[PDB]
Image (cartoon, coloured by chain):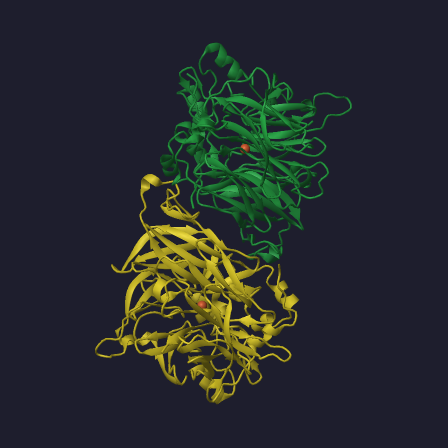
Chain colours: A green, B yellow
Amino acid sequence: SQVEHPAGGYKKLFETVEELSSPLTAHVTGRIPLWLTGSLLRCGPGLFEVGSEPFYHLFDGQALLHKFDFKEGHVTYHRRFIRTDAYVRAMTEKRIVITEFGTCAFEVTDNALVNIYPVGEDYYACTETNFITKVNPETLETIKQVDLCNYVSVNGATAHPHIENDGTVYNIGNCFGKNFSIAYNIVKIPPLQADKEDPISKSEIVVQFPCSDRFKPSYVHSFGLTPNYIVFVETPVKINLFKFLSSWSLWGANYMDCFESNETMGVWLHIADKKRKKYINNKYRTSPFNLFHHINTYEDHEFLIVDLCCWKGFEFVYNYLYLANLRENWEEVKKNARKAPQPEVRRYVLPLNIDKADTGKNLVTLPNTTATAILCSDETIWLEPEVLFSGPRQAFEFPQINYQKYGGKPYTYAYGLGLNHFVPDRLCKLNVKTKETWVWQEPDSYPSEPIFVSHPDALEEDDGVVLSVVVSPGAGQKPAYLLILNAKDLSEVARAEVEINIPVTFHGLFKKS
Amino acid sequence: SQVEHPAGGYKKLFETVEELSSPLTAHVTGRIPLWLTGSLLRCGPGLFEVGSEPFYHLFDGQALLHKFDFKEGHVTYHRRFIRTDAYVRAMTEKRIVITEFGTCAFPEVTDNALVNIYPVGEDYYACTETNFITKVNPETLETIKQVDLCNYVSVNGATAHPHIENDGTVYNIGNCFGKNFSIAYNIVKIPPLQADKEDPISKSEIVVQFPCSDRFKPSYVHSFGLTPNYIVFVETPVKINLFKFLSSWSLWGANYMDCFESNETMGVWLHIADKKRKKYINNKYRTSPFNLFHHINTYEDHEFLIVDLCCWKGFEFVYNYLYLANLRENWEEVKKNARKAPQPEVRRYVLPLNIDKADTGKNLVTLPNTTATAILCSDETIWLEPEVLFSGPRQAFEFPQINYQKYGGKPYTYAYGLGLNHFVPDRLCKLNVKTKETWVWQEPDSYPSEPIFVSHPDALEEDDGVVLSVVVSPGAGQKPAYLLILNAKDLSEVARAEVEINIPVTFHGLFKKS
Ligand SMILES: [Fe+2]
Ligand SMILES: [Fe+2]
């Protein structure tokens, strides 16, 4: 039966907070594993208005950097606003100065509210633009702004770079690479070398994917990577670059005003040979969905297995994530989601070898899937997915795996945040082979993306903990806590309670100390 | 885990048998329910060659009519070949005379009624998918009469899957040449037997007509959906090239299979008609390509139609995989042959009845209990995505059956099915279509038939009753075949009625209470 939230406590995920001057010791219930040593670092919006000027969209609030430190079974909590140009100019001018995703200012945003990742010995907070912000992972101080356009030919880059075990970083962004035309560029940033010079200054374009519309790139949030292949999924959510420059020059546009849906193209999937740095011209096609998060991608005989969190439909899912809608009472929140895209976890299987002798047949000869790929006479390969998880307006989202050991490789387990009509209200584990699921949830508690940490000496895939930040507003209750679950079955091992609210956070990482 | 059949006992499903002169008494184990009083009547092929001339395809063998009678806890088995023209002329001439689905006769439409049996008024008719249906005596299994549906209504053929309403009304669908220069599909209605006692077939009429996606190529239609207020028809990319049968059957000899092709670009078109106002509804429902043979059930839920289907993903015709030489191969080869086939999947589609243009670009499926979507586009098409109910690698839930008398056309919870393992029937299944919970019955080296549901007379719940299935079980010191009775609640075994003779594949049938 449908879990309801009449108390409306999720509204606290979208309430402005104050930063801390120094770390705060959390109150620990249960027992934190003595092997867990390091820092959970997470990004999200923390300031949702400047004076009496509101930010309107979920992705507009000013970037706040959060840290839970684990040492010898003890936990501290800390947070500092990132000193972006967006933030600094707002504090100076006492108004909204820089246009954000869904809020026009009355200059491209560097508001780094989305994620944080390592480059070399350094860490960068990011959003999805050309500006990334160097931050100190120890003190949470802001170090510098870096403009990716100084180094490589991209207009922006996702908040979901892939990082290989040696430190190499891959990312994607749109560009004008091709003559007369839009393209998508894979950027690679090397590991730090003996010369010790900034790896960002050695950035390069590895390969370029073509675009389905000369003048309209698709919105890209993440992408797939394996040892030999790069997978890029081109959705029907398009950026109409004509609509901004028109309004930026004529009348008051934000980033959300530039999006449109292409109703006829469906989804085009694309692969590139990572090592030979070569696009492969296989025209993979399927029906329309939005995609934000790839789960994992791997090679199996000569197929790519592509596990995705999908939303069925071509309407942009971000239309449903304005703060006024997310702050509404529960009955209204559910009503608002009634015509939304339906979330579904899907496995697609892409054949690498296309034999014309098989035209009109299913090419997916693997024994352990129901995914199909049909070779048509016009050379397109039409894909049908294997559904791994699907519940009515209950999304398995913000997925995470044992990335260090299983990213890009055959795997069994994913962890995610369960969204109930867009409200984060449970944690999920999914076996992608058997479709078995496990769930943690408590009434009136709204958790964040779960981050997996392996026991250091683990040989198994799910031998470790998942960490999640939980908001638990009520009479009597501590307003928030860090939750530590056993990764085997999502049973609770400990929690670390704080006496202050913590707003929504999107992404982060655990930094082993 | 993967179930293997290295002994190859499934080959006995496709082996010829002799009819019986009178019913055999079957050997009972367990307990036959004492409220089960009636006959299980099923059809299938029983003669797979005529002398030295083979039939090639699964749907070519000559129709055999089977009967298990239940009374006071005891069981009899009987079988007689149906005396169709195809059979009678093959016996007379000692050769294949009538071209079958996948077999050309060498030196005239088939009435080889191997597929199903159903009631019209006080009569029973065996059928295939052509214009010819065969009246049979359900007590003696004697053949009574050939009936040509073209004498009565303008269809070219009619499915082996009519819907029968509680009062006896029969609805069926078939292609026709209706509109000026145009193929269409006609819904035929056969009324209940009236006070006249006049033959209901002489009162048959066309209810409504669906348009065809292609002026000259109708799609293959195997079944359709029916609710109290609506008729639902699914137009798949499997097309019949009418140019091609009249063209190729004159050169040397084509069969029916030779006429099929697959349309690569249309996907699937779904269609609805208002049943009571007898009107086509012009909503252009569209989705991705699949083969469809069996609807499971259909019902109305607020302003939506819930359409549950057994699908095969892809546009290649599934029947290409059902030639007898391939089904008789050893198990490793049977598996290899199914590698590139369409993947089976049970899908629930949800069709909005009310389309508002202010919702253009959005999902119209506002129901609380489904992940199915229907997106209204600018060109007015409605693009559907299904909710997947069951999906296993080359493991189909097929030959679906429900508690039809009480739940057909209505909200429902349970379906029963035959599980196909790379096209080999090797288990029985039950599916809760709401929770997606399944139950399975299987035994090594046992190959069952479509399960048919019979309700307990005092039934309170939808699944209060039994399912009956005919099972082939060849092997050292085993009875070669048996009637299986399972409890419909949990598919636990209730009884078997064993026989000492082989029983080949049967496709469909019914339970006639008495
Ligand atoms: Fe993300
Ligand atoms: Fe059938």
Q: What percent of the width, then of the height, locates residue A432?
A: 59, 47
Q: What percent of the width, then of the height, locates residue A203?
A: 67, 26
Label count reads: 0
| Location of ligand 1 given as a quarter of the image | top right
Q: What percent of the width, then of the height, locates residue B387?
A: 45, 51
Name the residue nearer the viewer: B34 or B24: B34
Answer above or below: position of A392 versus B239.
above
Q: Residue B160 falls in which quadrant of the image? A: bottom left
Answer above or below: position of A269 versus A444.
below
Name the residue nearer the viewer: B484 or A208: B484
Q: What percent of the width, then of the height, locates residue B493?
A: 51, 70
Name the residue rendered at 58%, 80% in the picture. Answer: B479
On-image quarter of the C terminus of chain B: bottom left
**Is residue B482 visible in the rendered structure shown here?**
yes
Name the residue nearer the viewer: A73 or A218: A73
In the displayed structure, does residue B180 sit left or right of residue A426? left
Q: Seen from this angle, which residue lies furthest left?
A: B195
In the displayed structure, does residue B86 sit left or right of residue A159? left
Q: Residue B378 falls in which quadrant of the image? A: top left
**Is residue B183 visible in the rendered structure shown here?**
no
Q: Seen from this angle, which residue lies furthest top?
A: A92
On-image quarter of the N terminus of chain B: bottom right
